[PDB]
Amino acid sequence: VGTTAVMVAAARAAETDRPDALIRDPYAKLLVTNTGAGALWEAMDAEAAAMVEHMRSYQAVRTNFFDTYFNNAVIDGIRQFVILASGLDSRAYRLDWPTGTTVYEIDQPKVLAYKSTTLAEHGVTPTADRREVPIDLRQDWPPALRSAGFDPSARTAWLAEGLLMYLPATAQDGLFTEIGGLSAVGSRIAVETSPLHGDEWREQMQLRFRRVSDALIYHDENRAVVADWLNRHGWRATAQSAPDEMRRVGRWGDGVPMADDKDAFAEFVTAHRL
Image (cartoon, rainbow, N blue to C red; front, side):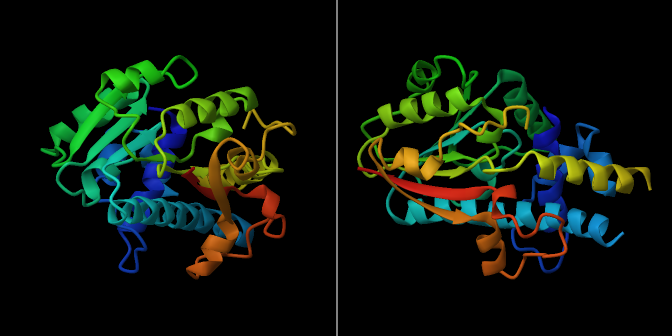
């Protein structure tokens, strides 16, 4: 399991531990105890303190947003779900799924094997029909999803959280093209975008975090804007900036360095298949 998957799960666990938790992920602590990279994250000036609080609050707010997305898709009748680069995401276990729901998780084999074995050791199994699809998303992944039982003629709700900024710009286009190819009318997708001007934030966040601890290689100016791309390849797409969403729920901390550039932060794009 990669460092990023652990860090975001540790953030979810930290949120879950608070009385005022925005989201509750009963499985995040379990998943970050059993790697060892989360002991440091478990442990973690004004700007330095604000960055740690931002890490937790950003992850809480992003988690709440994508939870709401899936929950609204269930309400709307959708019964086929796909979590792309699912990492340590426990939504297949912790959200309420109606009978007849299928939830596909796509990630590399070892990531999926870690989550399943780790959960099993704690007596945790899903009640929903959860289906693993072990494959690299830069490779020919549609046949793998299809052989796992996926029905392209059924409405699908797709999720791509914490993924795009870790894929080259050319790979993003290919991913979305394949997704459109597998999506029935009325399908939806929610996506966390790669920040418009945003590899500098990771540096200043690493710097503030390195001081707290001691105490995007694919950034591309040519990357397609996600809402714009979806809106000309068969979707109706809208964007909510992460800062706007954080402010919406009273979780934005303006003490964070780069607070005034909206381009240092992701957007949350939701789209409907035409």
